Amino acid sequence: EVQLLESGGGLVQPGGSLRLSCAVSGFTFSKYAMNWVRQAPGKGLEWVSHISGSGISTYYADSVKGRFTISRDTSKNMLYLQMNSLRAEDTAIYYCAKDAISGQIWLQGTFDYWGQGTLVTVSSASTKGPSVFPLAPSSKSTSGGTAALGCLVKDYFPEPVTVSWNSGALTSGVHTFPAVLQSSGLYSLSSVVTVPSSSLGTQTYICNVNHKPSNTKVDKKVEPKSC
Amino acid sequence: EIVMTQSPATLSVSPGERATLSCRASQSVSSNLAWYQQKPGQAPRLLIYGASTRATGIPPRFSGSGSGTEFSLTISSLQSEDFAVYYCQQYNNWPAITFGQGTRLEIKRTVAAPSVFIFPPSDEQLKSGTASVVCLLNNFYPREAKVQWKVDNALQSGNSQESVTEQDSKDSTYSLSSTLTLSKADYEKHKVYACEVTHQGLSSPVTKSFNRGE
Image (cartoon, rainbow over all chains, first blue to last red; front, top):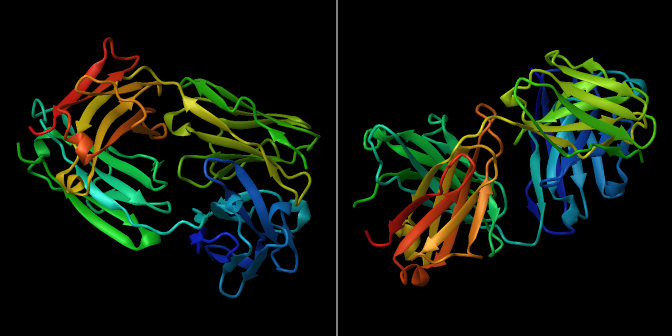
């Protein structure tokens, strides 16, 4: 089982520096060359950098040339990207990508395993944790129909937040909406779930909100209000 | 650089049918072309390399064809979990890898009307001086929908924001939220807050509403 685990992305000032890590497990690291590929929010894929299996050979896209440095430590199965003089256009999800066939140039140019990616946000705005409010179900009609409840995650920066329900137990019927950038410049999103109308008052519903950039972990319990 | 163009950037293909996606290169890239599938919130997964060879574990209904400058990706027996953005990528000029900008493949399922819910602002948020009123449209197709806010039967414009989920990988539906944001002072001036939903699988518009205090 091949696993690529990016880490180190976050909020950084324009002109600042950031170093990304990719933890590698499940294959012979020395046998394969490695790449970094990034994706700006809502945009396409852009190859950024490549390092040979040995590590002697490094290549860079022109858009990052002279500012980024790719490196590896095959001893401890690590891939690195040192990012300097960051600009707003560098804001993206950064993917760690492993080449398909071992060998050199003749067998290169294709990525068969990717990591889940880590987000880099280049901005001078401040970190701010969200407030979590309940979306209480009400007037649950027919008592055998379906009711909707959820959590409103408001006024945070930067992205992302994650929402789970009942510690990942409640999974079916969950819709976590994409965040919306408000007039204030802060983000806000809703996570909702549809449940049996008869379970209200029998099963307790708790949304687990995590905003890692601000070290904010919140569990909010959602119940029907009085009247 | 070799510019890869994927046109059209969107396609709507019925389930069970055959979807043909196009990728064109500014110069010949021979057979050094790959296809990737990116589902929402996930990394790309390699489908095709060598312009016709399937990567490991890729079912044979995914087929790549073409050479030179013209290429196609054909997905047979289209399934609801095939919703994704598909990228073609040339590696002829290695290491100057370039991607196309992708085609988003929507699964054209049958019409489904939304279930509509309204949520009043919490009293906790009400203390803070702001009231958020959330209208939910759940599990509908097609994506197009009109949501209107009525505050004491007065049309609201400029004070709401919408967010839509990606097409569901199982039932191919969308869900949408409309959020009305008012100051607590402006929230407490009026009485009736209504969400009016117009959509194709509803014969007449559906309204869900509440009254501030009750």
